[PDB]
Image 1 (cartoon, rainbow over the protein chains, first blue to last red):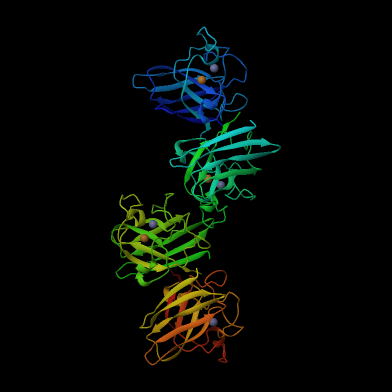
Image 2 (cartoon, each protein chain N blue to C red):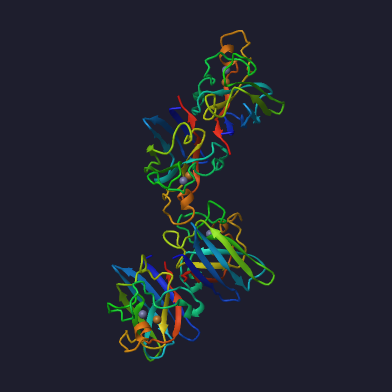
Length: 151
Length: 151
Length: 151
Length: 151
Ligand SMILES: [Cu+2]
Ligand SMILES: [Cu+2]
Ligand SMILES: [Cu+2]
Ligand SMILES: [Cu+2]
Ligand SMILES: [Zn+2]
Ligand SMILES: [Zn+2]
Ligand SMILES: [Zn+2]
Ligand SMILES: [Zn+2]
């Protein structure tokens, strides 16, 4: 697959759609998310496309290299670490990410996994506590969806 | 990926969880669907893991061998042709399928695609109209979900 | 039966010949209707090949899947829902339909049933009254005939 | 179908309605025909439900076993060979035939074919000439109709 899609849904008003496209050795991640409080929100690929108990059953960050949490620009990061998306005053975030580590095929493929938008900003591993090194202190899972093959 | 899961949701009361497991050289499909009308309902892997327009955006049946619609025992069938699930009088269908065409990795992978439960029985491609050769006259898509990697 | 024919007759000037042919996996509908008013007229397979009370005794639309009335492109439609034919200013309609639900043998066969051309356009089940969900508000039956096996 | 109907019409005053009902391995043929000259009239299922050029376009006797013409009681007969109906002095014939060879379903089905009442008596193949072995010398087609599925 060179194209993928994710519909983000949660138990509150947060929703959106994310598009994924293979370009060179990168994945180009675009889309939009509504209903968010203004400011940054952690945005991560979680390990499992399991929504049986909601976003919680997606498990931790997709992490096949067994590293600690960081920002997308960091060497020490989880594959699923895409940093922050930014909502404006209207609650809307436009997603425009280009990432070399995630993939839509092969070993680091995110097809069949879960995209999650978080309650709080991702501190990118620089928070000075244990949690920062795990989730970036991004807190609760506002909305999520399984990543699917798109036409 | 040796285990997958799917959570089925639609516009109506129909819901359920489908489990997939790679066992030996085959794929075992289990789970249950509730809120169905008594009797048979088409049960198919649709091509796209795309829920942007609910179940409609899943596209046609997964069909990488470019065949006509059939039953799961037929040579001429789509890879996604898993026949019928059967609901009892309480609207409950127990899912128990072993299938030789689907997989959980490589060309035949259904990870990132869509499981659909239909309004009507699948006629296994033997209805005698053109629709039968496409969908088995299974009709509308009551509920669907993207197939995700499971723990 | 791979070819069928229908001769349309009514109480007024409306007449025509409709040809049906099983081609590939589908049914191609051709022919022409004359004596019509300019514009659209509902064109439907009615259930009974019964002309004992003219076109009235043909009964409702052929509907073996127990659905509501729609257009021929719709999922929710009767098997007999072939939409509209269009008459030009001289009252002539050229019939050119390919249809996935009708057949010329087996469950979906329209052989021995009735082709009806209606007074008014078919609203494709979107008119918003109850009648729309039955007949598309197509109104009276200008002309009809029993579908017969052709050489 | 277990029930069928035919409205007989022609270019003259002969008309009637014929009813067909599946009973055991027979079809029970009933109805009435008016406007006839007193005496016997050949009564046959013709091959095609094609009325585009009137009764003539119905073609020959329905004959899927490729036999010669006889009476309904004869081994050598066409499937469409139902013998004679008898008009009284008032021009009225009451039809009451029970036949094992015609069918309303499967290979010998007469649904979509044509019922014809003839000018002259059917000589039942015993006329001593070539025509007798083809049509029973029943002569012209007074009235006919396509056989349709009835409620
Ligand atoms: Cu996260
Ligand atoms: Cu399907
Ligand atoms: Cu109609
Ligand atoms: Cu004859
Ligand atoms: Zn992380
Ligand atoms: Zn199929
Ligand atoms: Zn209709
Ligand atoms: Zn004969």
